[PDB]
Length: 101
Length: 51
View 1 (cartoon, chains in turn red, green):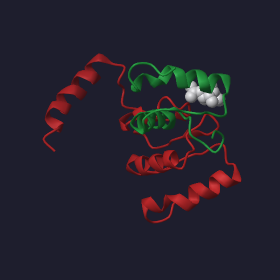
View 2 (spheres, chains in turn purple, green; view 1 turned 120 degrees about the vertical axis):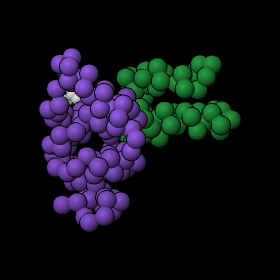
View 3 (cartoon, chains in turn brown, cyan; view 1 turned 90 degrees about the horizontal axis):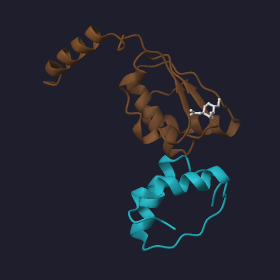
C-alpha cells in the first residue's frame, strides 16, 4: 500500500527494489502517478528490467519525456478516442477554452 | 569523443549502453560533467551497475 503522503514513497520503493519485484500494477489517479514516477526515477529504477502497468485511464496526459529514452515499458489504458477526426477537433476546441484555468 | 555540444551526448551513451561498457573515466570541466550526467540519468544509464 502507498502510505498516506505521496513523498513518503521512498521506503516502499526501496523495499520493492530490494525484493526484486520486476513487475508492478498501479491503481491511482494519475496525479499520484506523477509522484510515484518521479520517485521511481530518482531511486534509480527506470531500467528495461522493470515494466509497469497502469490502470489509471489517463496515461496519455502525463509528461512521458524525461523517462522515454530509459527503456522501461509503461503499458497503460486510454479510452478517449484520439483516433477519430471529429473527436480530436472537439478535443482541440475544448482545449482552446480549457486553458483559462 | 564527446561531440561539439553536450546535449549531443545521446548517441554515444547509446553505444556505451549497447556494448555494455560497465565502467568509465571522464574528463571535462565539470560544467560538462553536469550535462553529461543528466543525460546519463534520463538514458537509464545510472544504476548500481555502473561506476
